[PDB]
Amino acid sequence: MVPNVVVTGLTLVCSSAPGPLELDLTGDLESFKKQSFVLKEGVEYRIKISFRVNREIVSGMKYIQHTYRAGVAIDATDYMVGSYGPRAEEYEFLTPVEEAPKGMLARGSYSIKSRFTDDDKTDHLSWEWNFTIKKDWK
Image (cartoon, rainbow, N blue to C red):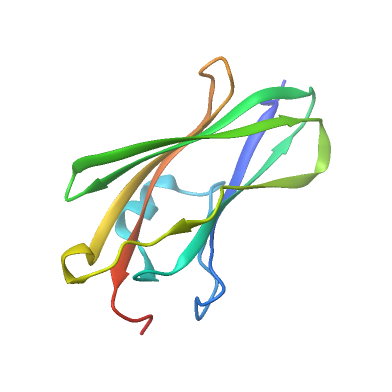
């Protein structure tokens, strides 16, 4: 009896980005710790989580991101994802607009521990990824 919820991807949505910033969450999660998305400082972006619901309607879904710099915790954000019914086609949850930090002192890599859960603390999927703040895209 398959998992009711399957998280399939994370996308850093940003118009200015020279190319797609996507993670296939159905693959090897450990690999992302060795990778990072370049993100120009000060730009606005959104995090898009792609997922599927196989058998039953869900409610009170939540997406959580804890941020770190050099392994030192900074903050935690809990996003309400909502309710979704079973469907073959993936759903796409979008966080509200966020802004990349800005300034030389803010540049560098940051790690993000992500958790896609429900109102029961059920861990549908947990993964760690990174973005690197730079002065320019290239």
